[PDB]
Amino acid sequence: GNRSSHSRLGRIEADSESQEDIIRNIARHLAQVGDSMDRSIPPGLVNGLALQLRNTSRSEEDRNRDLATALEQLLQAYPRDMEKEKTMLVLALLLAKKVASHTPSLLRDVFHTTVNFINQNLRTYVRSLARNGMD
Image (cartoon, rainbow, N blue to C red; front, top):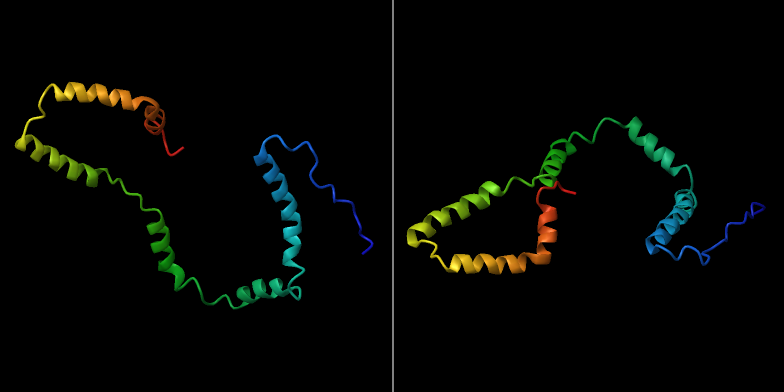
């Protein structure tokens, strides 16, 4: 082992700022040592054969996982509007609610103010969510 090489610098009073930055730096280091983990534990060239083996025998697979992927991908991305579902139930209740009784006054005005009081602070999260995309 004549490579020696000096890399045992380690951490030094300087990366204290931004603890998150420390992790990023540490990750990069591990990546370097992590890369050699793909050519130090196995006999060697084992991957080449594995990758090449699939290419040569590339006459199966995918055929059975074809539709399966669609179900997974489709299922994975199935947020749906949900508005039509919630709205339909809520809308129905409102119709029945009006029939059963008519939102009495006084309580509405008082309730509205009460909501404004609670709305504080919460509006920050709710407001951010509204008039905005996913992020």
